[PDB]
Image (cartoon, helix red, strand yellow):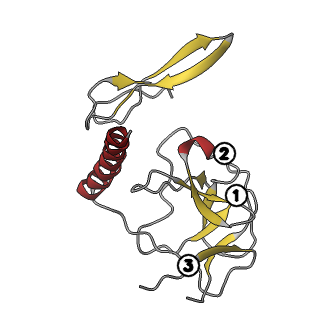
């Protein structure tokens, strides 16, 4: 809890980021400048902000659990919280809001190694084939 | 105590490069799919 990280979309290869004008958006690898792409899992939505955690040179202690634990995604730089637009399959746009909503809890479901392999193969193949198609068009 | 490298461990090969009077850290990488060569 409190550890900064980046969320990379496997299929597109782009990193989640927060621009002030158009909230959440995916950005290329060369424009992920940590300030806008840093996100954090929070146990509770209350403004604790303990911070000042010392990094441990080891595997650490397991804190966040798959499925059971309820997470709250918070932008590191701005402190904003991930929440839904609540107005329109489901197609509910995700926005940054300072106080969020009553139900912003997020569960985590791990993917299989085969599934992750297939997703990264898909992204590499679409990149290479788009390059080939553009070369043929040229 | 000083930690050691066991077999079943995940590691990254890292090196340093001195270019235009600065030091840059580079990790060995490879794609495996559609490209067998290794880059940094």
Q: Chain of mark 2?
A: A
Quarter of the image with the C terminus of chain A is top left
Q: Which mark is residue A33?
A: 2
Q: Is A65 or A26 nearer to us in this picture?
A: A26
Q: Using residue A70 as the reference point, say whether residue A138 is left or right of it.
A: left
**Residue at x 34%, y 24% (from the top left corner):** B38
At label 2, counting other C-alpha atoms closer than 10 Å, the crowd grade (few under 14, some 14-19, many 20 or more) is few
Q: Which mark is residue A76?
A: 1
**Residue at x 32%, y 45% (from the top left corner):** A133
Q: Quadrant of residue A80?
A: bottom right
Q: Is residue A37 visible?
A: yes
Residue furthest front as drawn: A138
Q: Chain of mark 3?
A: A
Which of pointers 2 and 3 indicates the residue nearer the eye?
Answer: 2
| Real-space CA distance between mark 1 and mark 2, rounded to the nearest whole angstrom | 12 Å
Secondary structure at numbered mark 3: loop
Q: Which mark is residue A59?
A: none
Of the image marks 2 and 3, the number of the one nearer the N terminus: 2
Q: How many marks?
A: 3
At label 3, counting other C-alpha atoms closer than 10 Å, the crowd grade (few under 14, some 14-19, many 20 or more) is some
Quarter of the image with the N terminus of chain A is bottom right
Q: Using residue A91 as the reference point, say whether residue A109 is left or right of it.
A: left
Above or below residue A10? Residue A80 is below
Q: Is A3 or A136 nearer to us in this picture?
A: A136
Of the image marks 1 and 3, the number of the one nearer the N terminus: 1
| Residue under numbered circle 3 | A105
Q: Is residue A1 visible?
A: no
Q: Are marks 1 and 2 in contact (CB under 8 Å)?
A: no
């Amino acid at each position: 809890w409190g550890q900064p990280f980046r969320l990379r979309h496997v299929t597109t290869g782009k990193y989640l980021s927060l621009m002030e004008d158009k909230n959440l958006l995916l950005m290329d690898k060369e424009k992920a400048d940590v300030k806008s792409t840093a996100f954090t899992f929070r146990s509770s939505k209350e403004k604790l902000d303990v911070g000042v955690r010392k990094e441990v040179d080891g595997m650490g202690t397991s804190e966040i659990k798959y499925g059971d634990s309820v997470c709250y995604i918070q932008h590191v730089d701005t402190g904003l919280w991930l929440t839904y637009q609540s107005v329109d399959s489901i197609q509910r746009k995700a926005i940054m809001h300072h106080e969020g909503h009553m139900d912003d809890g997020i569960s985590l479901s791990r993917s299989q190694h085969e599934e992750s392999r297939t997703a990264r193969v898909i992204r590499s193949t679409v990149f290479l084939f788009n390059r080939f198609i553009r070369g043929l068009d040229a | 105590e000083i930690q050691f490298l066991r077999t079943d461990d995940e590691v990254v090969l890292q090196c340093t490069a001195t270019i235009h009077k600065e030091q840059q850290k580079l990790c060995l990488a490879a794609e495996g799919f559609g490209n067998r060569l290794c880059f940094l």
